[PDB]
Each structure stands twice: as structure tokens, then as C-alpha cells.
Image (cartoon, helix red, strand yellow):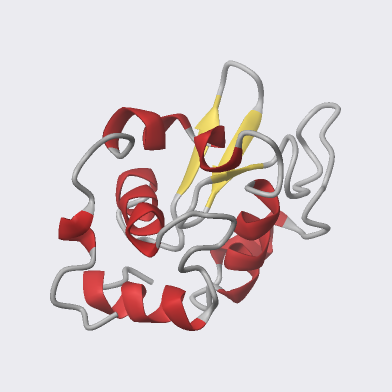
Length: 130
């Protein structure tokens, strides 16, 4: 599923993402935008280390979810990576919450640092009524 901007904003807010571990809703929107373009079925294989990023938050199979083919991987979210490819983003959000419970927080995603950190991210939630 490819979410519309404001449709996703309201959905994330209902799932308790606004201010989660000090992270504002607009930061989560900026993240989803540059990670997969609001597309839940996006996957990206990293030929360099044999892992794959899955879904709307492009979560990595090496630490967070299990796909059975990534070497020495762990499954901290206790999920099959398949769960992060559904149209319903509930599990992906539950897993994203887990990722930021680690010290790095939102910085765990490099794209956030490149395209969201220290930027005016207000534009991601403007007019959505959240």
C-alpha cells in the first residue's frame, strides 16, 4: 500500500507515535518519506552484507526481524520480516518503537540524519489536522 501523506500522519498519531521516546510525529513522517516513499511493500537488498530492509520504515533483517537467510541475524522485534510488508502498519510501528528504545534512538536510520536532522520538518504534517 502507498499511503497518502495526511492519511499516514493521522494513522501514526493513532498508533501512539507522536512524541514516542521524545520523537515528534513530523520526524517519523520525514523518515517514512525518505525510507520508502510511504510504500509498505518496499524492500531493499544490501548485497554488501546480505541483509534486506523491509517495509515503510525499511527495517533491517540483521537485528530486528527474521527472514531466515541473513547471516548471524537476531530478531529483536520477535517477528517474521513478512509482517513488515502488510498494508496494516501496526506491527511495523511496534517494531519501529523497539528500534528507538536503543541508545541511538531515531539516529539508527542514516537517511534520517541526511534528510531530516536539523531541518524544517513541519512541511510533512501541515494541513493534516494532527
